[PDB]
Length: 163
Length: 163
Image (cartoon, rainbow over all chains, first blue to last red; front, side, top):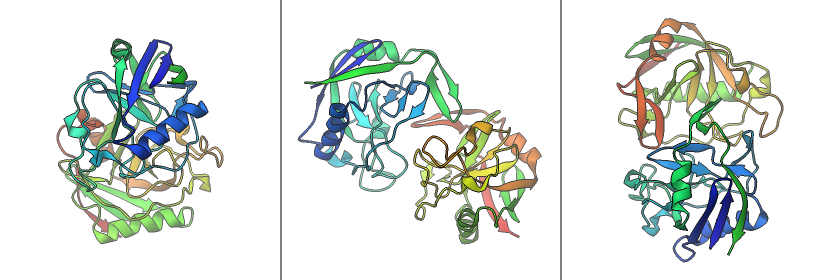
């Protein structure tokens, strides 16, 4: 289990170690190293998802390890409450950013090993604290340069407890 | 010179071959191959920029060649009318997507060879058709899945003439 202690409250998560081995191993290493402590949810889209794991307050970009392979062919779907890895246009580009589905985002699901089908890898799920997730999805946002949907007041993962 | 023949009119551009050699060579190869024909401006932000070169009508993602090295240390600034390469969080991640500055976006300028300073590489400038660029920046947009700021009616680069 992993708990995100945020300035809005705790979010407890169980990881799907057996269904997304490389992804979970990647995630837990960043958690154990304290990589996510003092990072924010920099992209919040009501009715869609909340994304975090890449910047410190003040939009300060953190350096990450090598990207991981997309494991979305594990068949897990992007339903409300699940956590998937954020990635660039390339399928094997995920590093540290992840997002939480606040609704079922079926359009994000894997549909085949192609550039257009690969989708987004679900590796975990919220088992407690969805009401904290729902409080965060509703905060006021704005543009912050290149970045859109940035919360006006920082949503901070203060520390993370692994198990 | 390169002309983008769009469904809103022509946009003529001169490239800075000597100041961004790898970038211009990359750009002109995609132009010559017909890579940009039938692609759209998928991200339009009024008062900021219009971005294109990666999708076909219907948000169909195109495959690209290997990424290029960031040449933003060439000192060129992101002023109104210039074209810079769009990239991911990593500095050496640009492929085919580019954007047009519709205002001076100083915050995008290179400030040192660091993850936080690298900025965005200016490789060209609009010499004719800025009024077409200004017509495009104002079109109605919406969310289209993972993508924000997508034009409701497609803004299409029909064909491209190189010189």
